[PDB]
Structure formats: C-alpha cells, structure tokens
Amino acid sequence: MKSRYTTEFHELEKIGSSVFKCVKRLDGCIYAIKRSKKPSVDEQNALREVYAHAVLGQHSHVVRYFSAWAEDDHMLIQNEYCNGGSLADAISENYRIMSYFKEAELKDLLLQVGRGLRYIHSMSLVHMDIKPSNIFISKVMFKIGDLGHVTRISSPQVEEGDSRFLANEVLQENYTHLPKADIFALALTVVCAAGAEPLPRNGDQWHEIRQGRLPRIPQVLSQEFTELLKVMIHPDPERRPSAMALVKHSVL
Ligand SMILES: COc1ccccc1-c1cc2c(c3c1C(=O)NC3=O)c1cc(O)ccc1n2CCCO
C-alpha cells in the first residue's frame, strides 16, 4: 500500500456511510473525502459526478471540488468540508425540540439554494437529487452537494432521485422540463425545514402533494411565501418558476 489517500491525508472521523473528515498533511486544511468501490454503465455514472464537480467549482452555493483519483478497487473524491453538517441533521434536531426555521430563515435557504441551482442550470446541467441530506451548511451558508445524479438538461436518459422529493413528470419519464424537477424538490426541501412531518415515499399522500397540495406546516407563514411554495410544486412544470425567476422573486 501507501495509498495517495494514506500518505497525503490524516483521517479524523467517518461522517457518512463512506465519507471521512480528513486533514491534508501538506496544506493543513480539512476536506471531506468520499471513498467508494470502483465500478460499465455504473462507471459512466460515477464519472459524471467527477465531470459535474470539475465544471461546478466556482460557486458559493455549490460544494467545491479539489481532486478525485482512483487506487485499488477504489474511487476517491476530495471536496470542501462543511462544518455545519447537512440540513437533514439540522431539521431532525429542530423536530426534536419543536423549534423550526422561521420565515426569514426559510427565505434565506430558498434564495441561497436557488442561486446554486441557477448556476447549475446555466451550465446546462440539472442536479436531479435535491433534498436536505444533499444540502450542507457552513451568516449560515447553504451549499448543494452530492452531484451523483447530475446530468445534462436535454438528457434522454435520467437516473431518478429520492422518491419523497421526486416530481411526477420525471416518474412518468417526461424529461422535457428537467430543470423544473429541481424546482419541485427545492420547495419540498423548504417544507421540511419549516417543520412538516417526514414526506411520504408513496401511497395516497405522495399523490396529493403531486396534485399540488402543500403538506401541513406547523407554523404561520405569509400568504405570499406560501403562494410561492405552492406554485413551485404545481403539477404543470411550465408553471413552476425557473431558478432565474425564483432568485428575482419579490417575496425574496
Ligand atoms: C466528498 O464528500 C461527498 C461526496 C459526494 C457526496 C456527498 C459528500 C459529502 C458528505 C458529507 C459531508 C460533506 C460532503 C462534501 O462533499 N462536503 C462535505 O462537507 C459532511 C459534512 C459534515 O460536516 C457532516 C456530514 C457530512 N457528509 C455525509 C452526510 C450526508 O448526508
């Protein structure tokens, strides 16, 4: 042995299951490094993650990429470490103490992730798996990470993201407005941060949201903000705002 991994980095802890928090011996900084079994169609998919990061490195609201390499039966990617953990962990803690993101904090989240998404989309890519466990926290700063489902906007083939966040047209394999799939998952992401119950994976409550009905939110929001979220989940993708229209919205 003597991995590049072993020799260039000191591993501190496992943070995801694998992803490790690591100090780079030479530069003194902390990075998150994912080590996955090297895969083929499964390899094409793994390399899109790398090609996506290598073009999505210049934005404040997308997690930065440093390097990627292969050794053994393993593939490695070294990203920016985000010391605030994921939004899914923040939301789960808030659930427990019954104190949620307040309206101003939900607007900040929506606008920051909105701007990462605007950038992603102006590179003719779509993220395809927007959800709280793929938003990282670092002013709070929210950064989109986990680019493993990224594809080009006009892709005829798509790997679908988490079903709790998945828009119906993508499930029906109508990929004509893929960017609006990211808009749909971002609304539901903000609904979780606001304090809603866990989203359903299927069944009758899944279809109700997909009819355009907001899950119940245990706090009082302005009619305006609520209107914006509702239109972000409209069953007709053409009605949802683009990320461009979103970051320039009056409500934000
Ligand atoms: C190479 O890393 C990845 C490669 C591909 C996909 C995701 C990650 C990932 C996971 C990640 C964190 C961080 C990243 C990242 O790219 N930058 C981070 O900072 C991070 C930071 C943290 O403070 C606590 C937990 C945690 N996880 C796992 C949790 C997943 O929900």
Image (cartoon, grey):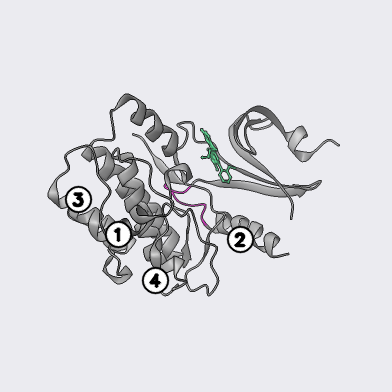
Q: Is residue 140 magenta?
A: no
C-alpha gap between disc 4 and disc 3: 23 Å
C-alpha gap between disc 2 and disc 1: 28 Å
Q: Is residue 58 magenta?
A: yes
Please state the horizontal and vertical placement of residue 34, each as a whole percent of the image: 64, 42
C-alpha gap between disc 2 and disc 4: 20 Å
Mark sitting earlier along the chain (2/1): 2
Tell me which segment is drawn in magenta.
56-62
Label 3: element kind: helix
Q: Residues within 10 Å of mark 3 (few under 14, many from 20)?
A: some
Front residue (pair 50, 87): 87
Q: Are marks 2 and 4 in contact (CB under 8 Å)?
A: no
Residue, disc 1: 233
Residue, disc 4: 177
Q: Amino acid at mark 1?
A: Ile
Q: Amino acid at mark 2?
A: Arg
Mark sitting earlier along the chain (3/2): 2
Please state the horizontal and vertical placement of residue 137, each as a whole percent of the image: 43, 37
Front residue (pair 195, 71): 195
Label 4: element kind: loop
Q: Is residue 170 left or right of residue 156?
A: left
C-alpha gap between disc 3 and disc 1: 11 Å
